Amino acid sequence: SKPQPIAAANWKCLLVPLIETLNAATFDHDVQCVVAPTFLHIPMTKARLTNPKFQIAAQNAGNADALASLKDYGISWVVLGHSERRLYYGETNEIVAEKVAQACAAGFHVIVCVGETNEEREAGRTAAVVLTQLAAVAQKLSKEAWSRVVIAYEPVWAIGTGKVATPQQAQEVHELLRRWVRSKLGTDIAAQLRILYGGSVTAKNARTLYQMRDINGFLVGGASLKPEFVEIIEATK
Amino acid sequence: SKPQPIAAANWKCLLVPLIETLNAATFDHDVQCVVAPTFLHIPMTKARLTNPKFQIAAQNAGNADALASLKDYGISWVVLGHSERRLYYGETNEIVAEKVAQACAAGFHVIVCVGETNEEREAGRTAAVVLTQLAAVAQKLSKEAWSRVVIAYEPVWAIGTGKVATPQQAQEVHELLRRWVRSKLGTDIAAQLRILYGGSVTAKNARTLYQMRDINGFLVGGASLKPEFVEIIEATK
Image (cartoon, rainbow over all chains, first blue to last red):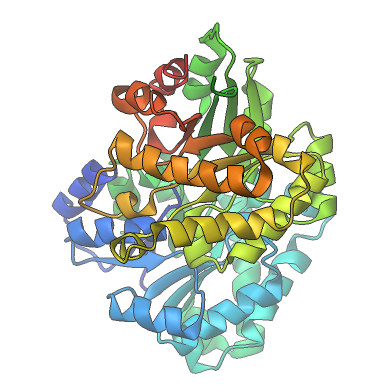
């Protein structure tokens, strides 16, 4: 069977109505929901979000001390490895991996993003790119650390322009990620590992994406600022 | 008289209608408009934005080489020193200052953000905080570099909660910034320097903010994703 799904909203972006909907929405299946606001918006989200299915996540892991204080503030999830950060803010594979290891060491659940650009895809380098990103991470983690790790695949190649990823192009990557994990860490860690889809997710396509075997949920961009995020969570049933 | 105003939109966040409005809007006074999308959204903005009053700005300055290629792509503005970056992503005063110096060295116009948190304000440290941020920057710049530098004040203390900055609390900071500049660099550089207001700007308050003597425009957050951004630009007349 699949592990527990996650529906994560990455609010990297007046949020009140959105939280209002999340608060009123009732989900009846096991799904961990996660909202990841910017740091300046964490207090306002924490002030208003009441749905007990939701954890609030930070978008960065600064220092062991910074993690400890986050954690004290009630935040124990973080999202790392965002492609924008990787490509344009000098977040090498090792830098992301060290952050994940620190966050893991602080007792956080961590959603680490992997993904290849359109140039890397077109060069047949999809596997090499995402598995190297993932290997950098794995090199720093304990066996037990993996229970609190979640992978998100961001098809950066699709963000750009003129490519829309199909469910099957999503599944191919997720399957490859999970096969590498099974190889390096065993069938145990592999089967329990959430791998979230971090490409274009909407009410329209969430259900079909969730049907793919190695898709355990979503790291949602745009669709997660609108009431439609509720339908995306329901699509994890 | 004031120098040329700037109206900058910081789109740190489906943008098409917004660009549509900017494209249709006609401004008849001298105002440099700037839109600063995320890097993954730069191609889509460049594909659609046609209003010749607008420059597109990047949100980071990685390397001399990365700047050179940005610049080749037609992007010669960048926004740096964002408070979120400063506080939560290890962007010390010196790190921001080095970025500004690199960007300046690459021939960019640069909007550098300064600003103090509510704790620092409450401790009487407003001046010490923003001028130290600014001094770090100034220490790296040539005399001529200042022609292409723009300062933005972000009242981080107001973002948080329960404080709304008045126009006069904006002006007090801007005046202090510009007095320090006049002291260190002369009346010439000081008078020509744009200092933008980077707190809560809307159609409702833009005009009153622009009336303050040392406010040369805006670095707009939320109000710049909506058609109201046009009114904010018009408020610079």
